[PDB]
Amino acid sequence: TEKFTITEHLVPGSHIREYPGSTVNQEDVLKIHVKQYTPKREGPVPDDAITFIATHGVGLPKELYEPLWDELLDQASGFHIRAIWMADVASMNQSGIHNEDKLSMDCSWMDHARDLLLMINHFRDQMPRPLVGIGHSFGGNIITNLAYLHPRLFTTLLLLDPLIQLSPPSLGFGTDAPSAINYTLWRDDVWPSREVAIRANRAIMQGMDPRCLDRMTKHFFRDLPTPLYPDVEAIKALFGTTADSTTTPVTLTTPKYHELVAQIRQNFNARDPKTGRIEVPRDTHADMDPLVAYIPLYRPEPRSTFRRLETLRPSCLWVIAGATFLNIDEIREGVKICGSGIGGSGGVPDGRVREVVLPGFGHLMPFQEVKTVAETCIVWLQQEMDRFRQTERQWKEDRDGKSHLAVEENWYKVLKPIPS
Amino acid sequence: TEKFTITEHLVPGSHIREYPGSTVNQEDVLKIHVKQYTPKREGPVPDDAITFIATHGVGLPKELYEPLWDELLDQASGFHIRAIWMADVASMNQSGIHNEDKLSMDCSWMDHARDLLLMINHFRDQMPRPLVGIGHSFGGNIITNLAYLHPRLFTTLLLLDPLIQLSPPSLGFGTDAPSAINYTLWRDDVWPSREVAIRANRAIMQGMDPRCLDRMTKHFFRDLPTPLYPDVEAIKALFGTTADSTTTPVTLTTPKYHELVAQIRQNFNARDPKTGRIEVPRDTHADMDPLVAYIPLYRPEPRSTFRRLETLRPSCLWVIAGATFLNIDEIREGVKICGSGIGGSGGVPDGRVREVVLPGFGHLMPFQEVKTVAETCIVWLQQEMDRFRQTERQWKEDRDGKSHLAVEENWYKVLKPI
């Protein structure tokens, strides 16, 4: 944005949502709001320039990642950027505004993977190989599932504190501490002014890069009226600001309820009332592991995604915040298994998977430590792009003389004729 | 079809193919040739009418399934048909002709699943719920992988002799008999006339419904020139027919090579030349199980698909030919595990998966036993659509009066404050 032309797009998402309650009508057409970042460039675009497909964390507007994009371009070494594409998940940020009359109270992370697959097919003429995935937080989970949908699509993945683990989050059950999820349900979500809203959200903004602070104050809050708060005057009356012409009340651009149903899903019907035994109800919770159904809330995708990691085809960089809320020990087992099985890159033994744990960094490192996050990504991208150039050349060499119309001679040596 | 209006479409498939050697250039846009079959109807379309998404077997033109479509409509009981959609896989049949300057010598079955997902999003306005998948042979494998891509997309699947099993096919290695796959590589693929081609292919057409015979003689053969045989006069010279100016040589519409690289994939580089040990080369064969790499040919999709069956979300009908050449015993283990695990329908224990083995039927039963294949499908569709109507109603009931904007009160009971 220092360094990029910005093009905005609104494209239809995937037909039929994973959970029927995620929209008002099951055939609703959700749109995703996309920003395409094209470097300001003198010369033509180099042949191996990367298309980046990026995904954000829950409630975090795509615009927050712009300083990270500027840093990737400014520090780029051994690769070029064709463009960076980041969409807002359909239920959040600017997508949520466009879809506000069609959204309802459910959310599957898997839908954004299908929404991105459609988007890539829509913009294919601007997205030749190589493509690289970047995913922050639940976006790390989504971009991994997009690689499961299309294994050879991405040359590599950059995961920034990805939500991929076996253990349910802490939810204040029994002796457990409440987590950010408890905070999400109960938090204030409307304020007499944007100034007051900023101060009420100081925890999330602490240590943010100033460039990220400006984007937060613009994108994280929305002036009334909204569907959730359709009556400006009733809210000015509640706060006693009816006389003050110079202040407009604001609410969360992403309603707390849309953050909540993305962070966690109801499991309100898991127990047979007569035996008290867990019986997974397949009509609504077929995706739920019975082992996690002991509490009335669950999140299926971290655990299903973890269990398929051995199949992950792209090479994968795992950037972990040392001061994260994720189950870091489970994540490091995920790194060890990543790409080691059938369909896999070859994983850690083949140098196709790397972990970088950044001590003292938090979950919001892409907004708090923009330069170090960028630098960690560049070192990996340069290694992967050296390998890409070499393997692309070896491929072209091995194919040079070969027919497009008939099989090579070795087939006639290995597959014998039927006895005449 | 007389019972259906036919609309033809040509739509772009999935960007970036699973195997780089599938096309001339990795960013090539392959198109799929689709037929949309809409019942001839006086009245409006009933509300729960089914969109069928159907996939064919290797080298079998989509038009061969038209008698089965007529039979499904004619025998329909307890369901309506909104439309049946069948596309030709990009490398075959009419799709292959449209794509002939872009195709190359490789094929992943997974790409047609992604091509179908795009097609469904393209035609979404004509495809409200419910959708049902029908897949014959490798099409049974593809439609299952489409259900893996989008678990809630299909209300049910009808698999007709699906290629879902653990074991490699027989390929004449060691003591094994050469199979249809050996036949595919070595078979005649050009004839001095269509009349001679038809006579030479009596074996494949034996027992076919007469409606299927006319479609076979039209769609199974193509007049030269084609890319593989671009020179009519060179082929008339090969057969010594140069004096007969009015007769045109024909070739297989689907080149035998496109059948072959869909039936089986080269594994020419699996063994370290020094240790003689299998080392899977991850740049080209990352999808290969080392346990099947002992022979220089493999097919990854039957085995990968089998291993994920416990996750299959839609209810599933498995129609098995009693005289099939598939590993029938492996298929019946697949049926038992189908939908039994996380993400699954609930499988056989919940009545969501059923096998029907049709004694003495072969792999080409959709063209040889049109009435019985249709009847087997109808009985299942009726049960599944009764369940759909009931579960759709219970869903609407449970949602009546609930907010689209804020969560229900129980959330404040289970999730404690700060």
Image (cartoon, coloured by chain):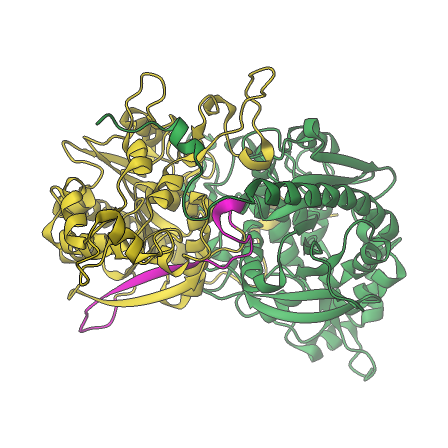
Chain colours: A green, B yellow
> Residue drawn at (48%, 47%), measured in percent from left and top?
B22
Tell me if A388 is positioned left or right of A116 in this view.
Answer: right
Residue A76 locus on image (x, y percent): 82, 53
> Residue drawn at (40%, 40%), measured in percent from left and top?
B261
Residue B39 magenta-highlighted: yes
The quarter of the picture where the C terminus of chain A appears is: top left
Q: Is residue B283 above or below residue A31?
A: above
Q: Name the residue nearer the viewer: A411 or A151.
A: A411
The quarter of the picture where the N terminus of chain A appears is: bottom right
Residue A329 locus on image (x, y percent): 73, 29
> Residue drawn at (17%, 73%), measured in percent from left and top?
B42
Residue B8 locus on image (x, y percent): 31, 66
> Within the image, what quadrant is residue B49 found in?
bottom left
**How many badges with numbers are in the image?**
0
Residue A71 locus on image (x, y percent): 84, 56
Tell me if A149 is positioned left or right of A135 in this view.
Answer: left
Q: Name the residue nearer the viewer: B194 or B393.
A: B194
Q: Is residue B264 above or below residue A224?
A: above
Judge whether residue B363 can be spotted in this image: yes
Judge whether residue B77 can be spotted in this image: no
Residue A288 magenta-highlighted: no
> Within the image, what quadrant is residue B123 found in?
bottom left
Q: Is residue B182 above or below residue B413?
A: above
Tell me where the magenta segment starts and ends, as one range: B17-45
Q: Name the residue nearer the viewer: A417 or A230.
A: A417
Tell me if A175 is positioned left or right of B348 in this view.
Answer: right
Tell me if A416 is positioned left or right of A243 in this view.
Answer: left
